Length: 330
Image 1 (cartoon, rainbow, N blue to C red):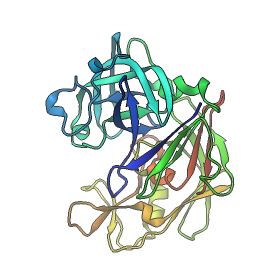
Image 2: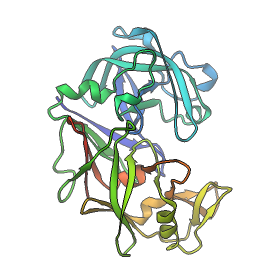
Image 3: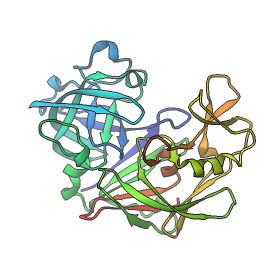
Image 4: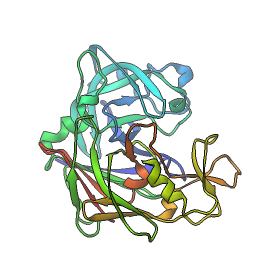
């Protein structure tokens, strides 16, 4: 089998991407944030504290004839941005772009933190990291991809995120018309439960490529590109007037700037992030100071190849017995 679904930016800055997902019978369609950095499929629901719902579409398991409460199961998750959510668990039928999994654990939120409430465009998350990170207790549950894998034509999914435009998540096949050149594959460590890999280096604009190992994660659920302080300083030094602002919480730059590109290495291959992809707009409404899309990972504890990086590539998440990651230009 295969599936194919369009993923759409939630706003004009690509602050996140949503993909429609069918849950239950009859189908209830929710727009979920596909997140290769976590492993829970959780949704706003009829059980979510009313004051914590503000415009989201909810899953109502009582209206699904295939929903079954998973007895005694709860979940609770905390993300890198400080946000959190928790609740109980149903199994139900879940379909993405024509690909169907029966018996999928659907984690129904009883509580969500303010950043989730305040974002009316995201109805939940669909985790695509490794199932070892799944938070359901006392019996850990599998991701949608893990449940689908054996049935797929090939045990892979691909992320093709757009810049200020829609893109595609495919399951079970590689669309050879969706990229240019070849796909370069690179080793993955699953020891931390992530799609963790090592970039071979970087360049800033038309500058010379610096060969240096950068261990990080391919994370569709993180908006920006988080890299070591040395790398990030080298980037922003090429932008007149750019500075790290402790009050804003990262590098900011004059909105009148033309940003240089940023290149990262995948083996001997090179992915070029155009400068415009690194502009996240005014720091506050009406400001002429703009927030940068490349930020320091210092004190995160890991480098994160988030949407800023991934949207410059066609990315293969290869779930073979030994997982690997593939990157192509597009």
